[PDB]
Each structure stands twice: as structure tokens, then as C-alpha cells.
Amino acid sequence: VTIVKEGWVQKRGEYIKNWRPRYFLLKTDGSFIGYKEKPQDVDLPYPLNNFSVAKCQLMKTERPKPNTFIIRCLQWTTVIERTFHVDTPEEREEWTEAIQAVADRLQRQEE
């Protein structure tokens, strides 16, 4: 398993509808793991966020924040969707490309 993309994002809270900073890693197994800081090697086993992007749906929007992407998976019945924004459209497209590419590989790995 390797890192496909990593970087800083603003993420809407899991319980409160605010934005907070997160450092996220997307891995080849579909894990999308977030930390409060760019992880020191020591802190890698203790993420704040840990979910799978397998079989996700993705949406890109510009309101309320420019360069937003939204991830939805069927089994996320509390949060419904997880919402992110980054500072440029190019960075946003990198994340949504990377996410879909990981999801597609996981689907071909079953087939």
C-alpha cells in the first residue's frame, strides 16, 4: 500500500458545520486518513479521520466555498457526505482524480 496523494485541506466537521484544517492521505487500498497536523511518523497510527473511498460518488462545487469537493458513500448514514475545500481548482481536481482512480482500481480488483 502506498500514498497516492497527500496534502492540507479544509474539512467540514463531523458534528459541527464549520470548516477545520486537516492533513489527509489517500492510499492505494482506498483508505482516506486525516490528521490535525502533517503527521510526524510517530503520530501516523493515531488519525482523527479514517474512512474508505470505495464506491464513492464525487461532486465539485464553488459555493459556499470555491474549490470544494464532496464525497458520498452509501453506508455513511449519519454524516451523509463529507465536504472539503482547497485553495486552487487544480488542487481540487488532483484530489477528485486521485479518489476516483483509487475507487476504480478497487472495483477492477474484485472483477
Image (cartoon, grey):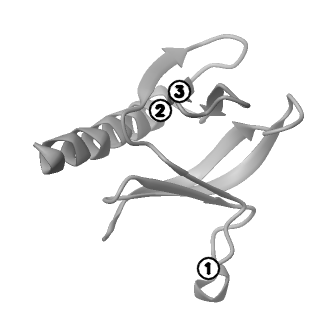
The numbered dot on residue 72 is: 3
SS at circle 3: strand
Q: Residue 99 at x, y = what percent? A: 37, 40
Per the model, the C-alpha gap separating discs 2 and 3 is 16 Å
Question: Disc 3 marks which amino acid?
Answer: Arg
Please give the name of the residue rendered at 47% of the width and 32% of the height, measured from the top-left corner.
Answer: 92
Query: For the residues marked 3 and 1, what is the alpha-carbon distance in whole angstroms?
Result: 25 Å
Outermost residue toward the left? 111
Amino acid type of the residue tagged 2 in the rendering: Arg
Residue 82 position, x and y percent, is 63, 32
Which numbered disc flags the more N-terminal residue, 3 or 1?
1
Secondary structure under badge 2? helix
Instruction: Report whether 39 appears left or right of 89.
Output: right
Q: Quadrant of the N terminus?
A: bottom left
Mark 2 in CB contact with mark 1 (< 8 angstroms): no
In the image, residue 48 above or below residue 60: below
Q: Which residue is mark 2?
A: 92
Q: Which residue is mark 1?
A: 45
Nearer the camera: disc 2 or disc 3: 3
State the separation of the CA atoms marked 2 and 1.
26 Å
Quadrant position of residue 93: top left
Residue at x 60% of width, y 78% of height: 44
Residue type, numbered disc 1 = Pro
Question: Residue 18, image x and y in percent?
Answer: 86, 32
